Length: 207
Image (cartoon, rainbow, N blue to C red; front, side, top):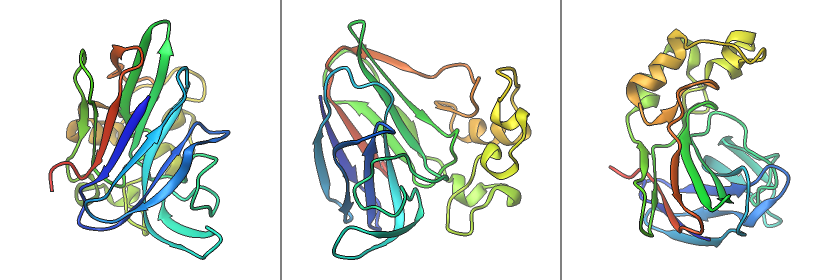
C-alpha cells in the first residue's frame, strides 16, 4: 500500500514510519512546510505507526536528537518514538480488511488527519490545540502534551491489569479529540477500510 505523508505545518517536521522492530520504507525523513513524502508499505503489515518529530538535529550519518518522538537518536526510525507523539496506526490486509486509527495514548505533539485516498471508508482527525490547552502536569518542556501513563506510571493510567477506566487526563484528550483513542480501553475509534486501500497522513491539516 501507498501512504503519502504531507507536512502542512508552518514548521519543519521529521516524519517517521515504523512497525516497532523495523523501519517502514526508509523509516524517516525531513519534511519542510508543504513537502510530501511517498512511502510503500508491505501488504499484511501489522501494527504500523506514522508520527511526526519536532526540533530535531541530525549530523551527516543520520544521528542526533529530536525534542518529541525521538527513536533512539536516528533519522531513519527502526523503533517507535519517545512520547509525546500523536500516532497514525494501521494494520493492513487482516482478513480482507485494513484497520486505521489515530491515538493519543502516547500523548500529542502535532495535529493530524489520517484519510484513505481510495474508496470505501472515511478518515479520522485530531486537529485541536491540545498543546495550548494541555493540563500543567502533562506539559512536556520539549513541546507537546504527554499522556498520564508516561508521566505518572500507575496501573490505572497504564491499564497494566487490563482493567482501567477513563480518568481526568484521558477525558481531556477525548473532549478535544473524540475520534482518537484517549486511553488503552477507550471505546474503539478504529475505521475499517477495504483491504489494500491507500492513504494520506497530513500534519497540521487545518493551519
